Image: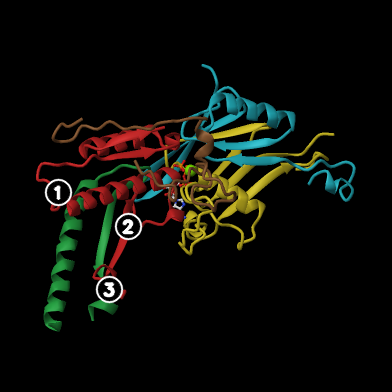
Chain colours: A yellow, B brown, C green, D cyan, E red
Amino acid sequence: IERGKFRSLTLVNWNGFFARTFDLDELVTTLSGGNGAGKSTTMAAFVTALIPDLTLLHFRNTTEAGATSGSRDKGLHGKLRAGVCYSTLDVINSRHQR
Amino acid sequence: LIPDLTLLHFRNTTEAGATSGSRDKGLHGKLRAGVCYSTLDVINSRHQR
Amino acid sequence: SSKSVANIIRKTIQREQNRIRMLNQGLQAVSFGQVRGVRLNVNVRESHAI
Amino acid sequence: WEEESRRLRGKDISPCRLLFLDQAARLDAKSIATLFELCERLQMQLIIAAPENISPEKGTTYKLVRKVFKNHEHVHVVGLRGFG
Amino acid sequence: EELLDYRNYLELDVEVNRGSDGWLKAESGALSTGEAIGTGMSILVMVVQSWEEESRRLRGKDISPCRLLFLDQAARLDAKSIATLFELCERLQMQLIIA
Ligand SMILES: Nc1ncnc2c1ncn2[C@@H]1O[C@H](COP(=O)(O)OP(=O)(O)OP(=O)(O)O)[C@@H](O)[C@H]1O
Ligand SMILES: [Mg+2]
């Protein structure tokens, strides 16, 4: 059977990204750039698209991963710009449905 | 630098602040059977070695 | 004695603020990602100032 | 999890597979090659991040650069290729 | 007893001049890995300098204690951040062990 795949990830009005669509790879997609480029932002946006449960979403730094920082902020709000924002996934199903 | 068994905890870089999980501090397995040594050499402002 | 205690607290607070402000000068213009400067902000809490 | 849900799901659908790895620079070349071979053997998609391009000859790659621009920020994305 | 200590009378915060924006309170959740690591090193050198200043008056006038710090998994930082860290350590005559 042909397993479904994640074609692309689209980010709208995000912090730094206005409307950017990264076309994902069949096996591996890599993101590079100096510190603060916004890779972690892309990961966070994806996972938000996957599990929009607001209680769970907590974007701690890679440092203090699971160490309580007492910031009281999940970090998602500062990753979005004012106004509307979108985070979407295109998936090709094993039934070849987009 | 700090030869205190209470404080020395060589947890993995991952889980840098997370709970112990296990009871070992991770130091024993870094040693070998027998007598071992860890030494620093310092030159003061007075230049005493 | 109470007046002296208050004055010594004030003097120590001023001295520590000055020392921290002095130290802060060395961290000016540090380029880290989008970070360009670091400061240690020291203040006197109102609940204790009063 | 996939195996357990094999009954409820239809016989014609295989669920998508995808994982992440931030700060990939903590892994060396050998470890990353092993991870790649494992993921491809398991048909597992991976999204990895590292300040330096640690996987130049496999999958797709992007490079992001953040520019201050008229008192706000913009991220510019450029594709990368193994050979030139 | 908490009130009896002068330090408690002081509020201390860490602020960063992040990008186009002004000085913002340093929240671990509102920064990238490299930014947090760099701010941590900055505060650590601040602490070391403060400790040396405090201890000087109880030491020989011609004693300068050694300063040495670590950085494991340094690969999380880019070349620019590493160069800035090296510049900082040199300016502070501070030894680094980076993995
Ligand atoms: N919630 C937030 N509030 C404010 N600024 C944020 C927030 N989230 C991210 N930023 C800033 O956005 C920029 C990108 O952050 P991000 O963590 O996504 O970068 P990155 O590419 O993953 O970085 P690194 O590889 O160094 O960890 C950085 O300047 C970060 O400080
Ligand atoms: Mg990151």
Closer to the N terminus: mark 1 or mark 2?
A: 2
Chain under disc 1: E
Could you tell me the amino acid type at mark 1?
Arg
Residue position marked by numbered label 2 in the rendering: E14
Disc 3 residue type (three-letter): Arg
Where is C6 relative to C42, above or below?
A: below
Q: Residues within 10 Å of mark 2 (few under 14, many from 20)?
A: some
Question: What label does residue E59 carry, if any?
Answer: 1
Q: Label 3, on which residue?
A: C45
Q: Relative to residue E66, is residue B5 drawn left or right?
A: right
Q: Quadrant of residue A95?
A: top right
Task: Using the image, name the chain to which the residue with label 3 belongs.
Answer: C
Task: Where is residue B25? Give x, y as percent.
Answer: 52, 45
The amino acid marked with disc number 2 is: Val
Closest to the observer, B46 or E69: B46
Secondary-structure class at tag 2: strand
- Residue drawn at x 50%, y 34% as measured from the top left: B30
Are labels 3 and 2 on one chain? no
Q: Which chain hosts label 2?
A: E
Determine whether the beta carbon of the residue marked 3 sits less than 8 angstroms from the nearest atom of ligand 1: no
